Image: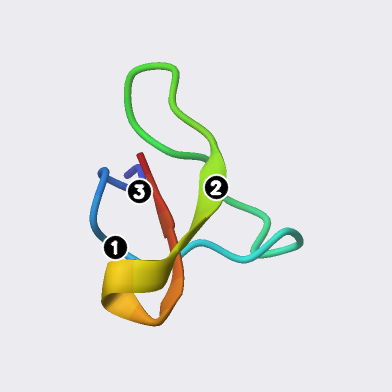
Amino acid sequence: GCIAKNKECAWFSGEWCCGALSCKYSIKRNLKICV
């Protein structure tokens, strides 16, 4: 159970992204997802 580099990610979602990526803003996705 982890957030991939494409799925939304809240700064307080409580979960973490896969591998070792963080939650950044994606202009192209006009939202906030991991990378």
Pick whichever of labels 1 and 2 is earlier in the sequence: 1
**Could you give the CA–CA distance between mark 3 and mark 1, rounded to whole angstroms?**
6 Å
Q: Do callouts 3 and 1 mark residues in contact (Cβ within 8 Å)?
A: yes
The amino acid sitting under disc 2 is Cys
**In terms of image quadrants, where is residue 7?**
bottom left
State the residue position of label 2: 23
State the residue position of label 1: 7
- Name the disc covering residue 3, or none: 3
Q: Residue at x 35, y 39 (%)?
A: 35
Q: Residue at x 35, y 42 (%)?
A: 2
The amino acid sitting under disc 1 is Lys
Q: Do callouts 1 and 2 mark residues in contact (Cβ within 8 Å)?
A: no
Q: Please tell me how many numbered marks the rendered image carries.
A: 3
Q: Do callouts 3 and 2 mark residues in contact (Cβ within 8 Å)?
A: yes
In this rendering, is residue 28 above or below 15?
Answer: below
Q: Is residue 10 left or right of residue 18?
A: right
Q: Secondary structure at mark 1?
A: loop
Q: Quadrant of the N terminus?
A: top left
**Could you give the CA–CA distance between mark 3 and mark 2, rounded to whole angstroms?**
9 Å
**In terms of image quadrants, where is residue 19?**
top left
In the rendered image, the residue lying farthest to the front is 27
Pick whichever of labels 3 and 2 is earlier in the sequence: 3
Q: Is residue 25 left or right of residue 8?
A: right
Q: Secondary structure at mark 2?
A: strand
In this rendering, is residue 12 above or below 28?
Answer: above
Q: Residues within 10 Å of mark 2 (few under 14, many from 20)?
A: many
Q: Residue at x 28, y 70 (%)?
A: 28
In the rendered image, the residue lying farthest to the right is 12
